[PDB]
Amino acid sequence: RKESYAIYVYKVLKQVHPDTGISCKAMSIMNSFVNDVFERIAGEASRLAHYNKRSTITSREIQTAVRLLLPGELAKHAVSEGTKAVTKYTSA
DNA sequence: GGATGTATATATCTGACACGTGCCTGGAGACTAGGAAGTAATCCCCTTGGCGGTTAAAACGCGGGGGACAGCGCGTACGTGCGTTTAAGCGGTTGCTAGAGCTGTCTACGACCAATTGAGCGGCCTCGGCACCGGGATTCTCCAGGGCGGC
């Protein structure tokens, strides 16, 4: 009961590299990275909601936080990823 | 004798004080639930002062040469100044649209709560692969017999 991100990072690793392992320190670094990106995007979306006098955080605020924080092709590819995930989640 | 410098008085300009009003946001009073303080138990990590042994890192000394720094020359590129151009800055036209603010209505979306159950965490059993032990096949070193030579 430690509430980590290790199993999902492991499944993503088996998606991109099915025959590659990962050490415990590298897994801790990946968990810290996911937590850092989560709190950056959530803080930017919270600030965006407060700037526009909105009481809710929607996918638009998350999208704007992604386009604000992520640079270059990372931003547009993450927008395409999140957009098609939201489209798949809505239709079904 | 005429006009100029200077002092006191009066009207006007301007920042500041108080009065008035709305309104809406903070304060007063009451109630309630849960966040956090406190308590006890268990277990593992950290503290302080020691010992022993390995060993690789740290320290010290010394020679030498590479590099930092100073000086000098030179030539070029930037500062300085002036005359000319040009465009910024201001004021102005003329319509339309974007956007803030306010009011109003409504609806879909998210909070909330109860029941459920299935994905996450731990252990247990098994397989894939690596490794330990016993047995069979192949090649290397050696001891002895036969033949020849000498007195």
Image (cartoon, coloured by chain):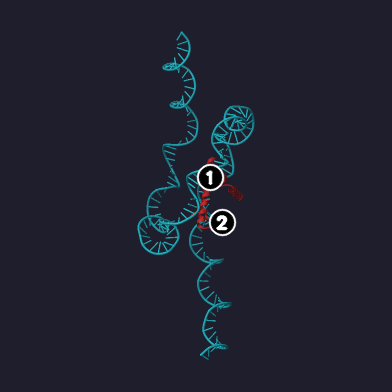
Can you identify the residue that label 2 sits on?
A13
Q: Identify the element where label 1 is drawn.
A: helix
* Local crowd size for mark 1, using a 10 Å CA cut-off: few (<14), some (14–19), many (≥20): some
Spatial distance from mark 1 to mark 2, Cα to Cα? Answer: 28 Å
Quadrant of the rendered image containing residue B105: top right
Between B69 and B105, the one nearer to me in the picture: B69
Looking at the picture, how far across and down is residue A29, in whole percent? Answer: 51, 54
With respect to residue B145, does B92 lie above or below? above
Can you identify the residue that label 1 sits on?
A44
With respect to residue B140, does A43 lie above or below? above
Looking at the picture, how far across and down is residue B149, in whole percent? Answer: 55, 88
Q: State which tag comes first along the sequence, 1 or 2.
A: 2
Q: Which chain is red?
A: A
Chain B tint in image: cyan
The amino acid pointed to by label 2 is Leu
Dot 2: chain letter: A
Residue at horizontal 53 percent and vertical 45 percent from the top: A44
Between B87 and B28, the one nearer to me in the picture: B87
Residue at horizontal 52 percent and vertical 51 percent from the top: A33
Residue at horizontal 50 percent and vertical 56 percent from the top: A25
